Image (tube, rainbow over all chains, first blue to last red; front, side, top):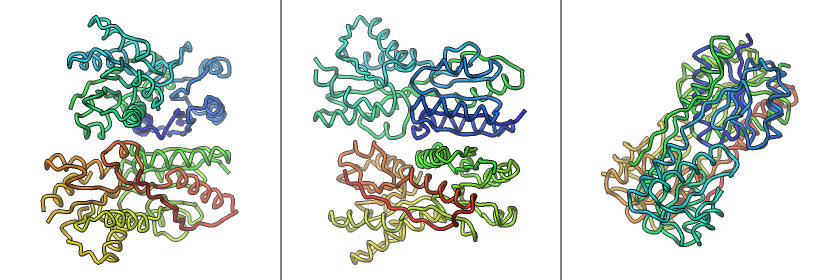
Length: 261
Length: 261
């Protein structure tokens, strides 16, 4: 009834979220909704403040890219009729929708690709260990390695992640890494030349997130592309259904695609 | 009096604008304003629709990253008392504030660096020829060349820019290029290997925008860093003054810094 929706993002400066936001804004606009923006910069205290601020302003609903931390307040501080849909990371709160990527499958595909190239010492640098995304991407890694009968040393796993990369690469160090996002891939690239190692001959990398600069390297960095704008567009579509009473909250898993270039 | 401000951005998916939006949102929040977001994707017809949409919702004012096109409709379709501050590109409408970078200075500094390295065949790939940013970044280039007594062939100038790069680099082609943003730098990188040329020994590059990937290259790509967050914060600060009657619209030029890595 107000035709305003609240979009709260954990990091607008990260291009993943910016493109999610573009899909949200494009859908809302096509349907005649306005979009209130808040950026939390991964601070849960700010996320809570924006939730309360957006609620008091009586937005019709919230699209939330959650920051790392507890989200129980959402279930006790808000009416059960206030529609929320999460992107990227799930809430695990009854009634809250989620639009999420197929992380397990994408990671398993990326790592198989490395295995098919002849890597056996393969590691993984992920972001914060507690996240749904880190957890599922790590899981895909383990499943690929397991199916190939390749053992995985825990010292090969780390949770920018430059320091993590630097630690796993100064170990029987891996010849290959799965990185869980473009920003971690940045930190891995920083670790290589901190350690004097050579992207390519010394270490190969498969990453999530399809950034143009990854294609400029030699070899081109293979990536798992996430359907960022579609995540945004579908969250807004599910939020609108919830608001106008034409549909339910659900967990939607969207396809990723492996790009080898 | 509503405590809502309209942020209209020409391309939220471009990291430049995402970081400006971040600065705007952080300053609005600190002052108890909310931010409605529109993304135009560089379409002036969408810009005008957002402006009208935001005005009818009675936002207190607008921060506008202008899309290329005519902006006189601002001056005729809005009350003179409606505060507007532009970022990145100026409006040239009486009463509208602007928060811009020091484009001439930063470009001259980057090109002088190339000249101090021993480049004499130096070109420039800029974005759309009309824009204030392209115009000023080109001017800085010419002033550096001039001061060094190095002649510039027009055919070294092009206004992604992959095609423009491909064109200037298949000419007495330059050994170095100024590129006017990270997105143009992507197109020049694309051109290099379309042409079979080598970043480095064949063509060097200085760019605006400080992206982490630029430092992974060999050599590292020197950049003119823009104060993106501060541009957003100050544009919001100016706009708030204008709304609460505590200050005036003006043109602010913000310091950029040259990063060689």
